[PDB]
Each structure stands twice: as structure tokens, then as C-alpha cells.
Image 1 (cartoon, rainbow over the protein chains, first blue to last red):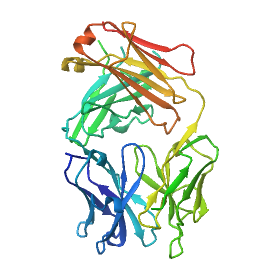
Image 2: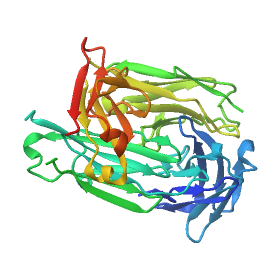
Image 3: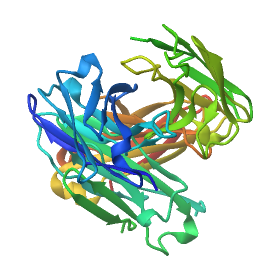
Image 4: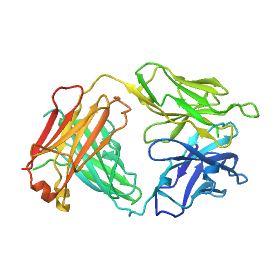
Amino acid sequence: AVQLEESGPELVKPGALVKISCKASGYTFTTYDINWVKQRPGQGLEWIGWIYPGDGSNKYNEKFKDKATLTVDKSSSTAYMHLSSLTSENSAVYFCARGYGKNVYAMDYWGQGTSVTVSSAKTTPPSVYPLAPGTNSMVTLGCLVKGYFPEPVTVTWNSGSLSSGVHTFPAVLQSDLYTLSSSVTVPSSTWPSETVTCNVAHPASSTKVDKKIVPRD
Amino acid sequence: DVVMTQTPLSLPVSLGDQASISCRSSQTIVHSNGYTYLDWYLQKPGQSPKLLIYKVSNRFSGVPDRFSGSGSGTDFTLKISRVEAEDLGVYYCFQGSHVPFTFGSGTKLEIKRADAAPTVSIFPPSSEQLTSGGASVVCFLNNFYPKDINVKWKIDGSERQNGVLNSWTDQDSKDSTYSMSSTLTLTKDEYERHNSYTCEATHKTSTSPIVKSFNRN
């Protein structure tokens, strides 16, 4: 199974340097191009360059030649991107993709991406607050995820058991802090006769919070 | 640079109908060696871009035959026949013939469905939050079609404008509806100063607003 594992989120101060890493498995690393693609918050994909791990040859897009440096480590089958002189406008999601080689003619396997935030703000974990009602046969419960930094935050209900009726909203940033909510709808005969719990992850602070939703007294 | 221009930027297609995306290009994507490295990608909300079509017409393994690509040199097309709800996301044409490799701008595929009223739910601030000295009031507006919606908050029956943050979902991959969340954030003191808190949605599906309220006691 061809796989590409990219590093976790990064918070770095303006005018700093980051080293983004991408570990390959499931194919001969040294015989396929590795590509990088930028994606800014909002829309759009932009190709940065490829490296050929076999001999370390590369091609860069002119625009990124001064900000992006591509290296490789054969021994660990890892590809690396270094981003330099960091501005706010450099805050983006950067992708890894295996490209040209034997029987491959496009970017067929992509990494999960690495979100890079450039801010002078401080990493801070979320406070997760429960949201319970004040028989319809359908009841909507929720979690408020408030005051975390940086993005992202993943929300999951009962360790993934409930996928249906789950809405997690895009975060809204105010005063260097993000807030999102997530809602889940379940049949009334299953709450609060059974446990409903939201699971919030914040990879940048390495924090998982699991809040159980209990009725008001 | 080979400019990739995609038309349209938005594609509203009904469920089951054909959807076609046009990609035009500055130069010829026909490479020196004779091959045409023109690819189509798909980026679903919150996911990596995935390969759909390579070399103009060849579809990547695991991609259903519902997707087919055609065209030559300067002009290209991708057709999705019999569209399903999970097909929504952003479609990119991409050239790998002339350095730098370039993507088109996005073609956002939205689907059309029947009208749906929002399920409105209001939540007082949790005990946990009040203890911190903050008081968020969250209102959910769930599973409605189409996009357009507004929220009016009332503290003590009087419209409150300052202190409100909103967030809208991308189109849902299952039932094809949109969703929204609104959060009135106060201090425990400001919150304790008043008594009634109402959340009201106006949608095109009703004359009257859906009013959900609670009293602080």
C-alpha cells in the first residue's frame, strides 16, 4: 500500500524557518519524483517543485526558488521541504505527492498535507464546553470548542461511532483565538438513556478532550 | 507559464444529471516526446486532492467509469454522468508538460435538491464556561436548502448585533444540505444582567421566523 506520511502542524514566528517532512512507504522511493503543492486558506493549488530521490536532482517553480528548498534522505525514505523567511501570506497547507516514474504519469498518491501557520501568537489548547437542551424523538446535542490556536481541531463523536447527523463548523478566529462548534443529532430514546461524548483533538498542542453531554438540572 | 482557465468556477448540477467541466490552456500540453500530461484532480472538503483522470482520457484505478476525460492540445473536458451526492468538491485540471507545472483555478461542484427547513436549536452557556467568566450562547441552524439564511439575536426581546460570530458548512456529502451556527458571546456579568435570549432564523421556506428561546432561570 503506497503511502505518504507528512509531519504534523507547525506554528512558527514571522521571518523563521520550517522543515516539512514526508515519509514514503510501499514503493521504491528512489525511482519516483516527489512533488510539492501549496494550498492557501481559501482555494487553489500551486505546484512548488519535484525532487528525484534517486540522484537528488530537482526542478523548482521560479516563484518558490528563494523560499522553498527541497532535500531528500534516501536511508529513511523521507523527503523534506524547508520554507524560509516566513510571512503571514506563507500560512498554507503544503502537500506531498509521488509523481513521474515507471507506470506513473501523474500525482497519484498524495500525503495528508501539513498545515503551516505563521503568527506571533501562542499555541493554546481548546476549552470544550458541553451543549445540552434547556419528546421530539430527535434531539440535537453539541460541543463548543473555544479559544484554541492554531488550526486545526478535529471533532469526532463517540470515538467515531456516530458519523450521521454530525456537523462540525469551520472555525472563526477572533483576537488570536479560534472557536468552532460541532453538533450531533440522535433519536431521543438514546439520550440521556445512553452516553453521548464529543472528542476534540488539537494536534498542535498534542491535546485530546472528551466531553460527556449531560442534561441540565 | 501555461495558464489553465477552467469554466465554470461554479457548477450547480441536479442529482443524476450530467456535469461537464471545460479546461482551456495558454499553450499546447502536447509534450516534446508526444504524450499529453493533462490530469484532472478532485479535492473533497477536508481531504487531500485525489487523482481522477491522467493523460487526458485514462482514469486512475478505483475511479468509477462515471468519470471520463477528453480533448486535445489546447482544449480539454471532464464529464461526470449520473452524478451522486458524494461527488461534490473542487475539480482541478492540471498540466505537467512545461515547467512550471500548473493547475487550473477551481471548479466547485454544488448539487441541487428539494427545499428544506432548518432545524433550529438554542443552548445556554454551560456551567463550566460560566465558571471561567465567559458566557457563550450558541444556536444551530441545521440541514437546510438552499445556501441563503440569516439569524437575528434578541437579548430581552431587543435585537443584539455586536458580539455575534457565524460559521457555515460546506455542502453535506450525504443529504446535500447546508448548515450554519451562530454564537453570541458575553461576560458572565453581561449575561447575568439580562433574562431572555432568542435565536431567530429566516429562510425562504417559511414566512414566519423559527424562534427558539430560553430564560436564564
